[PDB]
Length: 639
Ligand SMILES: [Cu+2]
Ligand SMILES: [Cu+2]
Ligand SMILES: [Cu+2]
Image 1 (cartoon, rainbow, N blue to C red):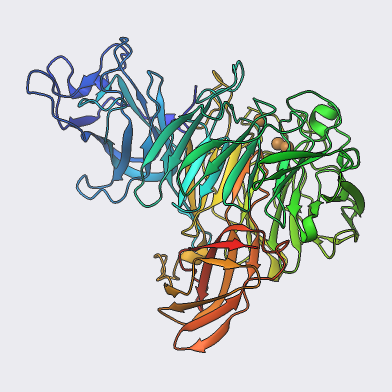
Image 2 (image 1 turned 180 degrees about the vertical axis):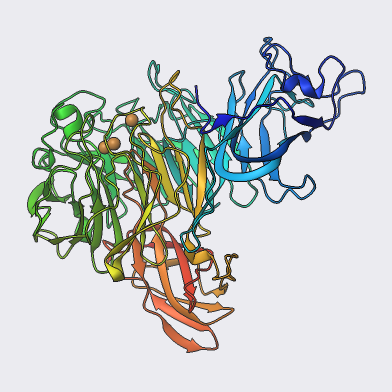
C-alpha cells in the first residue's frame, strides 16, 4: 500500500469538470465517496476519444494542498487505469503553471497517490496523459485532495523541493544512465515487495529529465532479482549489479545500448555488500551477509575485460566488521568503500576501524586506524553515509548512522577523513559540530561546488517505519566547515530511499519502504533545486553554457579545452552516481584547475592518477562568478 502525506479535504462543496464523461459514469462519480462508482470518459457512445483526459476540481476556497489520491475502478475491469499523468494546481482556474507532480502509476487497481510539497491552491487538475495499458479511456472511482495542517513559504536562499515524480515502483536502488541522462531505478521481483521472491526477475523504471517520461522494464535476461545489491560503474562504462535477492548473480547495465547483459556469477554469494570500482576499472567487493549465507565473506574482484570474478580470500572482512548486536548478518554490510590509488580500496566505515584493502595477488587488508577526533573514538555507524567531495585532496565526509543496523539511535557524528597513500593511516577530524539532525538511512550527494547535500533518514533506525523522520536536509560546505539547513520537504525518506545528482545540477531523492502491504511504500521521488540555481530575486538564475568541448572522451592526465558563453570562475568533474541502502561508491568530485585561454576559452587536465580520477563517466560542470553551474557535459574518463 501507500499513503497520503496530508489529510483528506472535505468535498461537500466541490465543483468538478471532466473533458468527457459517459452517462452513468459522470464526472462527479469520482467524488461521491463510493468506491463502486467511477467517472469514465466517452466510449462506444461518443466514440473513444484518446487521452489526454482531464479531471479538474474547483475546491471553492484556498487549500494548502499537499497531495491527491486516485482510486481506480474496483469492478475488476482495467479500462481507464491512468498511466502517465500530471497534476496541476491553480489559484484562478486558467493559469496552471507547471505540474506539481508527474510520472506514471503502476498498472493495477490499487489506490495511487501524488504526494508533493504544500502549495495553496483552489483548483486542482489531474491530466491522464495515457491509459496504463495504452487504451483510449480514463476512469476514476474516487479522487481526493489532501491538505497540510499549515503552509509556510520556503525560506529564500535555502533551495526548493519540487516537483514530485510519480513512479510505478519504489525506487530502492537507482543509477544515472550517463549516455542518456536518464535516472534508472529498480525494486525487486515486485513493484513494492522483495519478500517471497522466486528470484530471477527485477522490475525497473526510468525517468527522463528532458521529456519528463517515466517508463518501466522487467529484466529477466540476467536471471537476477537485484534487490539488496552491490552497485558499481566499471571502467568500461557498465553498471555492475551484484547479488542481493539472487545472491550469486551479476547483472550488467550498459547505458550506451540501454540494455542489461548477464555477467559472471560472483565467487561468493552476497547481499548488502558494497562494491567499489578500482583505479584500473575493475570492481572490488567484500562482506554482504544479508543473503547467500552468514559467514566470513572476504574480498573478490570483477574484471570487465575477462568477465570474471576472482576471489581475494586474504582481503579479510574480519577487520571491517561492526559490533552489531545482530552479528555477522548486519556487521559486514554497506561498507564505506572508495576506489583509490594502485588498485587499493579504502574502507572508511561503518566500523570504527578503518581499513585499506589491496587487490594484488589473493588480496590483503591493513588497518588504517580508527575513525576518530578530539571528541573521541567514533562509534560504529551502520548506514551512515560517506562522500568523497574532493578526490584530488582525498577528502571524505562521513556522517550519521547508528551502532546497530536497527533498533538503534542514530547520531550526529560527522568526520572529515583525508586520504594519502594506501597503507598510511589517514588523518580524521570532526566535521564542524556534526549534523543538525541525527539520522540513519539518510542519503547524500556531492554537488558541483563541492558541497554535500544530505537528506532524509530518521533518528532511530526502524526499517519500514516512518517514525522520527528528518524533513530538513543539510548541506555541508567544506570551505566553511559548516552545515546549513535547507528548506524541508514533506515526504519521509527512510529505509530504502535513494538520492542521485542529476546532470542539470539538481538532486533526485526518492524511494523508501518496499514492504508490500505496509502503508510506508513511497512510489515517488522529488527534485531538490539547490540555491546555486536561484538568483537573489528568487527566480532561476541564468546559467553559463559550455558552447564547445575539445573531446567527450579523455585519458587520465589528459587535457580538455572548452568554450563558454561567459566567464567561468570554477569547474568540477563529478563522477556519475549509483545508489541503494545509503551506499554510493561511484560518486566523487574533482575540482578542476582552469587555464584561462582568453575569450572564454578554458582548458584543464584530468588528474593523472586513476585512483583519483576513477575511470568511467563524469559530469563536467562550470560555474560563473555568481556561482551558478552550467548543466553537465558528459565526459568519459579512461586509463
Ligand atoms: Cu533492504
Ligand atoms: Cu541501512
Ligand atoms: Cu546499512
